[PDB]
Amino acid sequence: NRPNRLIVDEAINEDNSVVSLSQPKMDELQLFRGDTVLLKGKKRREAVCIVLSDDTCSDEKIRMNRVVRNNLRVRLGDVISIQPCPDVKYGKRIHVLPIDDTVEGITGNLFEVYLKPYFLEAYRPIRKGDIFLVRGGMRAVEFKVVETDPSPYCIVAPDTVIHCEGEPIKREDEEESLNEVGYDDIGGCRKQLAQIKEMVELPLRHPALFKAIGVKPPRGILLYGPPGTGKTLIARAVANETGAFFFLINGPEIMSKLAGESESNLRKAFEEAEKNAPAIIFIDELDAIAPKREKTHGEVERRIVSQLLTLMDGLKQRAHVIVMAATNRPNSIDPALRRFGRFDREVDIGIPDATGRLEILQIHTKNMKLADDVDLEQVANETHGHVGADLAALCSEAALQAIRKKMDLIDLEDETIDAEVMNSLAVTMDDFRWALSQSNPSALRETVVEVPQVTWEDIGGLEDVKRELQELVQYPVEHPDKFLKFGMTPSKGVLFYGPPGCGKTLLAKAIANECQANFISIKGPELLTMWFGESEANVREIFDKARQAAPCVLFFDELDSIAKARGGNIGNGGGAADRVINQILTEMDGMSTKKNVFIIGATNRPDIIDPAILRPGRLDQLIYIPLPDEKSRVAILKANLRKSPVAKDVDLEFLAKMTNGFSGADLTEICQRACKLAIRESIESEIVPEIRRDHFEEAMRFARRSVSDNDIRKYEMFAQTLQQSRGF
Amino acid sequence: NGPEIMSKLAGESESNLRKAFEEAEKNAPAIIFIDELDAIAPKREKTHGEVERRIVSQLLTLMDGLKQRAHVIVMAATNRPNSIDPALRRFGRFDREVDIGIPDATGRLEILQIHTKNMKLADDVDLEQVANETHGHVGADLAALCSEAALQAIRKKMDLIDLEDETIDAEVMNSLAVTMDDFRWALSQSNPSALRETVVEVPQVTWEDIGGLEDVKRELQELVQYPVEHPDKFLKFGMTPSKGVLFYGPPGCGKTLLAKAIANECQANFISIKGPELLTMWFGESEANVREIFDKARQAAPCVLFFDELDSIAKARGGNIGNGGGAADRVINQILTEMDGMSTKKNVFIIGATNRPDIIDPAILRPGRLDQLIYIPLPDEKSRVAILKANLRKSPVAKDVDLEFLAKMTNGFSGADLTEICQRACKLAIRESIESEIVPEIRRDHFEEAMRFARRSVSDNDIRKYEMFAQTLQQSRGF
Ligand SMILES: Nc1ncnc2c1ncn2[C@@H]1O[C@H](COP(=O)(O)OP(=O)(O)OP(O)(O)=S)[C@@H](O)[C@H]1O
Ligand SMILES: Nc1ncnc2c1ncn2[C@@H]1O[C@H](COP(=O)(O)OP(=O)(O)OP(O)(O)=S)[C@@H](O)[C@H]1O
Ligand SMILES: Nc1ncnc2c1ncn2[C@@H]1O[C@H](COP(=O)(O)OP(=O)(O)OP(O)(O)=S)[C@@H](O)[C@H]1O
Ligand SMILES: [Mg+2]
Ligand SMILES: [Mg+2]
Ligand SMILES: [Mg+2]
């Protein structure tokens, strides 16, 4: 019915007004690639734009830029009306004006810096009263045409003239300031944003329908994660991207008040939220006001917690009020809040990965002007423990370093500097390198949940175990139909055992990568150092974090360190299977099979592994990784020498047949030593850039075997008899 | 409401409690419900403000001043019963305690029906399957799951059908139906709250899931079913039934399955406490949780309390000798105390299982604690056929598969080993199907290939040692 209603969501083209459609859509509306289109919105106002031909987006969804959502007064998920007008329209005179909210502190002719390299070679349309934003001069200005030839009858053409005024127009309250945070201002959290949208937009955008349908809304969203991960940013963006009244409660600000006055503040907050339409209450830093009532001193604090619980419980569905809260210490929150009816939805705003932090870097540098040598992808790769706040600080420091080299070379001593020199200020990759040099990552200690970068190509040989890992991991998650047809429940666990340096860690990471599943690595020393504080909840938290990351692989590396805590099965006579390992067994037994969490254990001490690991249902797929044979050694050398300029005379299979008892680590050490000899040769010759046959000969001269023949025999013995182990 | 009372100022919450009790006494037979009792009445030893202690004392005074003539019944709800001040749980204040435990599969199916009765479900919706697939869910979790499935159904109908009307009519609401895929999606995104909680239920495994072991099945029937089904014979002959059984033998021979199956046949509640669970609850030095296990078994009578993987417990300090000190410590002494402190007339039966009879501490084996020593050996040739048949019930096995051929080709294999063989053959069949897609019957060739890599999980020396302990384990104690 009425094939002209289009559903609106956030766009993917990071530019000015360019709408994107789906495969049935350009055929249904018979519109071409570079077509001028007219968009019709609510409140009797219009927008003219350019279509973008997209097919692999969805079945029916248009993609709308935040620049032109405000031109139509339409928000996310709203319905829009469209009308193709494939007529070329050229404007003669456009009377254009800035706004005195984003142009303060900037003087001169802002057109030669903003509107010149934004108009030409674009051919974009302009309508009456359109607020379009141009980024430049390490800042962003939204801009307003106020007078021109009849609307729209305007696209960007060279015959369109420009004129400087210097008189910005005041911003009325009818339109929303684009400088405010939106969904385009968050990077690295799209799954979490998707969950937040699914929980929030329907109750708020459609309150009457939701109330009439009589179903429970999620009213207890609790955002949590490490500090500086965008929790406040996400909450304020969700507030802005919906037409919901937003009341903010600050933990410290509430607790700074006198006794009996903070309770009044909470009551007034909830009363105002109930009064003012669908609304969002955001309690930032919830742990400030609501710590655990068992661990707290003053009775005023306990009254605060009880008052918050009462207000949460007295929140009815008829109120159409959604309460979000943010805390970076979710375990310090009083448990009564995290129950049903108060805070039942929990969203983990985790540390961004490499792609996510690259997106954050782009979001923070979009206003900045970067030199051509700036590789934001490289910066994202080189930043590991950084969070969104860390990346914003890094970008700010790089910008300030660039300024420091331009405030002295160019005397910027003028009181209010113009943009004619601000564009000349550019941030080089060296500035980013310097900023990265002086930067303290906050989330270094945090566990990493990401898809690892290592592929099968980084692993030499081991084809059989690659196939077995594929069958054990990929097939249950890719073809559940076969498993349910044949009735067999997939095994949830694999134990890697064998001599050291044979690729046990690489195999787990690579099988994580091929499935494109999240990977969590918990090393034995990490467990033994978290447990020394007698914190039984952190090992539980590891399995919890793996649960929300499904499909995920939970890899316990270096189990030998765990099994060597008290020596082993005998050890001092008492069992080294204690502390964490019993809790690990309990967590393995307490996780459902239908969950896509796969557990992999690795150890190079199969003698002292406790039998309870090997029980069916915990880790019963015993995979033995042996020393590489002659062909696997060639493969390992090829994999390790991918990044090095190896000379053509190097005979890799000669090295493979000259190394017999060497592991993958030993061959990597040989390659590293030969590369280091090449580096030394280059250094000496400076006072050639190809690692040669002679370097490998010299490295092989000092090459050493890290696995004994007795060790090989014992590993082969355990390779045959480790299923027995348990029992005696 | 606990928090609502505690949110008031000092001296005003006491007034609220007094007014509540006065109104209840005034208005006929009445019920006072104190929701979240732990909010207002924590342990007076562990509390800070004197206002809170006055609140607790006022509640105690009001409970004690409640006369029979008042016809007032006070109910209270708490999810932390052990945090309640002990003075409240005594006679005259709160003497009746009801444990609203986690629902089982049938109960959670009933909850799903109660929450979906208003909803319109498609014909593919199998609420029984959803109940089976939800384990740690409680009634609130199931209500949330149903609500999320309904909202997922709406999301696929608010866009396909423009429901943009302000007040939608029912002529299209009926057209909105919740499919089994919506329930599957909701179950995919759902966090069960009671995953860590102990499960008290009748297990699903029957005798048909166990191959062979007919003699131990009969012995378990005599030990468990007869005392609870025919007490008259036992009182006629004057013998008190033994309250305990210890399962010992090589690993993977069905010790867990036997306990669960004997629980199922009696239709009795089953509680499984594994050794690692005990060793991880005890690391917090919580001596009350192991007591709580026996308590929970007491209200679940007739119940079977199964302690699985006692080898892990006995390996905490190595064993009887171990490091020289005794590995019988921590939980095991409290387990012995709890076993000795439970009345015989209670229908709680205790079963222990271990595959390390060498390091089991003798105090377990004392008459009155676990004196029925049942040895589960490796399956023999016919029991292997039975085990293979039991494991292949759910798989489409081809007719050419010779099960007794596999049984006679496997000699030292346990039930776990045969299950591993079946799983490997099934996985080869899955691989064949995957390859052929780019037939739906596990064949003789698959079993041949699986048997090619089949492995024996019990050594001949282990078999000899288990046979030695099968004959001499009653001795054990003494030296
Ligand atoms: N994911 C992100 N995407 C973009 N910018 C981000 C992101 N995370 C943080 N930032 C930036 O870093 C700033 C840090 O503020 P927030 O992360 O919102 O504070 P927070 O997340 O509540 O952490 P707290 O308050 O210290 S516990 C934000 O204002 C953004 O400028
Ligand atoms: N099959 C292999 N192919 C390529 N490189 C390998 C291989 N095996 C080992 N290496 C190298 O040796 C390093 C150690 O590999 P790991 O996966 O950690 O092996 P491991 O079995 O965990 O033994 P350790 O204790 O980690 S040295 C890798 O980072 C590689 O540089
Ligand atoms: N008699 C049997 N009949 C059928 N399946 C069996 C039998 N014995 C063992 N199995 C299989 O092996 C698995 C383990 O059985 P359990 O009852 O756990 O034996 P167990 O003596 O407790 O030894 P573990 O330590 O649990 S492997 C079961 O889940 C079945 O798949
Ligand atoms: Mg914040
Ligand atoms: Mg490693
Ligand atoms: Mg078992």
Image: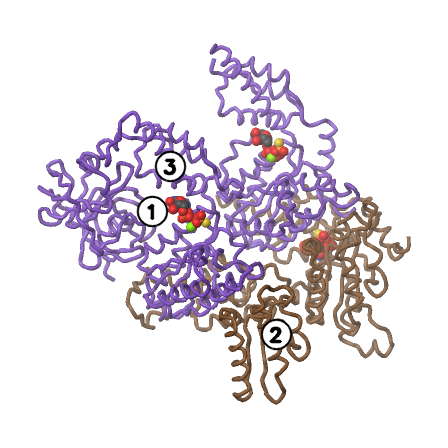
Chain colours: A purple, B brown
Instruction: Where is residue A562? Give x, y as percent.
Output: 67, 42
- Using the image, determine if residue A395 lies above or below residue B204: above
Q: Are marks 2 and 3 on the same chain?
A: no
Residue name at image x 68 percent, y 46 percent? A614
Say if residue A669 shows up in the picture: yes
Q: Is residue B341 left or right of residue B140?
A: right
Q: Which mark is residue A395?
A: 3
What subunit carries mark 2?
A: B
Q: Which mark is residue A184?
A: 1
Distance between mark 2 and mark 3 Cα atoms: 60 Å
Between disc 2 and disc 1, the foreground one is: 2
Disc 1 residue type (three-letter): Asp
Query: Looking at this view, is A430 or A562 the one in front?
Result: A430
- Using the image, determine if residue A293 lies above or below residue B400: below
Mark 2 surroundings within 10 Å by alpha-carbon count, few (fewer than 14), some (14 through 19), many (20 or more):
some
Instruction: Where is residue A133? Give x, y as percent.
Output: 24, 44
What subunit carries mark 3?
A: A
Distance between mark 2 and mark 1 Cα atoms: 57 Å
Q: Which residue is mark 2?
A: B57
Between disc 2 and disc 3, the foreground one is: 2
Looking at the image, how many numbered discs can be counted on the residues? 3
Query: Looking at this view, is A301 or A115 the one in front?
Result: A301
Q: Tell me which corner region of the image, top left, top right, bottom left or bottom right, holds residue B84.
A: bottom right
Q: Which mark is residue A564?
A: none
Say if residue B386 shows up in the picture: no
Disc 3 residue type (three-letter): Cys
Disc 2 residue type (three-letter): Ser
Distance between mark 1 and mark 3 Cα atoms: 18 Å
Instruction: Where is residue A282? Give x, y as percent.
Output: 40, 58
- Using the image, determine if residue B287 lies above or below residue A496: below
